[PDB]
Structures are given as C-alpha cells and as structure tokens.
Image 1 (tube, rainbow, N blue to C red):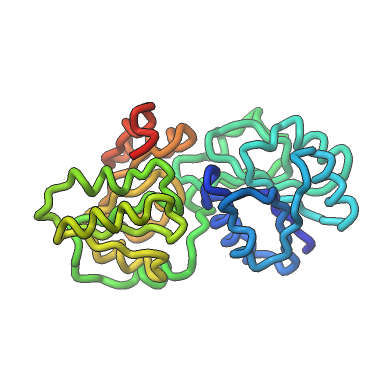
Image 2: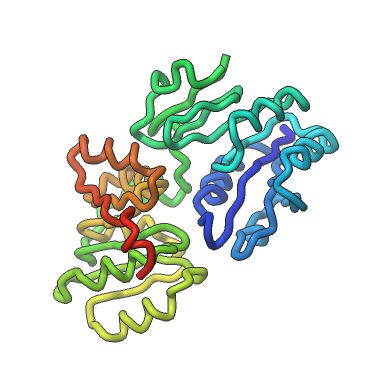
Length: 281
C-alpha cells in the first residue's frame, strides 16, 4: 500500500525481528525495509528493497518516509522510542504499526503483540484510536506449520532443541551436552551460528545427536519429536499450533511475559540462562 519496515538484524540483535517481519510483509504488495548495515545482518536474504541507513538519526528515517511517500511505517525495533514515534508522526503524518513484546507504551495507530500471553486490555493508557492487536489470533506463523499441524507423526526424537536463528549464548550445546546420552536428540540451527563448528565436533563425540542446519521443514522435526526445548519467542506460537509438549527457555529479559504465562499454563520454563555466567558457552 506503500509500506516501510523499520527493523534491524545482526549477529548481536538476532534474526527474529526480520523473520517475523517477512511473514507480516506478505500482507502488503508494496513493501520496503530500512536497515542499518550491520555485521551479520540478513539484508541480502530480504527479498524487498532495503534502504541502507547511514546513521541512527531519527531524522534520516523521517527523510526516507517523506521522500518516498510511504503510507505505513511498521516498526519492529527496540531502539525506536515513544518519543521517536511521536516525532515521526508529527513530522510525516505516516500511519504507524508498532510491534511490542513486553507491554510497553507506543505512539502508534496499530499496536501488534503477537505473543499468546497478551491481551488488548494490557495496553489501556499505553497507546493512543489505536487498534490493539494482541495474542495468538495475530501469530506470525509460516505456512508449513499450518500444513504440518494436520499430520500425526510417528515420534523419532526424544528431544528437539531450537534456540532460534543465531543462539548467541550457545545454549544449544549446553542443553544437549547435559541431556542423557541415551536420549535421541535433534538440534536445529542456522549456518550463521557463530559456534557451529563446535556443535558439529560435539555431535561427533556422541551417537545420539543429529544436527539439522538451515532445515527447510522445521515443523515436521518438531512434530516428530516427543519434547521440544525452545526459546520463548516466535517458536512458542509454532509449538502451540502443533500442540507440542515443550519446555521454554527465557532467552533474554524481554521474553519474561511469555515465560510467565507459559508457566501459569503448566509448561516447564527455565530462567537460569538470564544469569550472567550463562552468557557464553
């Protein structure tokens, strides 16, 4: 409709914003991204025009919105503040859809919280007229999962481990390394994983660990595993749709709301990897 996503990815930030944004992007026919060129970004994976920002100045973003006459700005970025959104609105009049994950205020026209814990009432007083979209109704799930949700798979793995795109803390290794060596384990990670070679070496020491790198059918892997061990973000919605048995790892502070809700719903949740000694493995 002439839409711009403001979202970054990198080795540090992770791929989670861009990946979910790509699902949402399918809703619109004229889509562009505005990204900082950062080490390890997904800029070349993104199949839409990507405007490269020369600075973190909010006025550079404002310039791009004015010059290209974008009609909707989709913000999926922890670094864009309420004051920033206010300024963008004042200076451009663009419509703003803001992603939110922790229940924080936004100056937006559409608030989008894709996490199953979230309810529109949580945003009373935190948003402007704003359409508040919260919860599992608004999950951003790739099509393969809807297909796979209909299958009833024979189980091939005792455990499926997936920490997401990058696993900067290298939790996948720590988790696998302590599970009994009599348990059949699948691990899914990307070829961009900074500790991949180490994960491969570890797998070689054992007979029970199978690695899947840039796997095209993660849904089936999940469906054929008895228990999942997943980070507490986008994978949670995918796991819920598959009606999987899973343990959720609160990977970063911002997943606390999801983790808290999962525990209330009776899922096992682990918070210890937030502790400083677990920041690397």
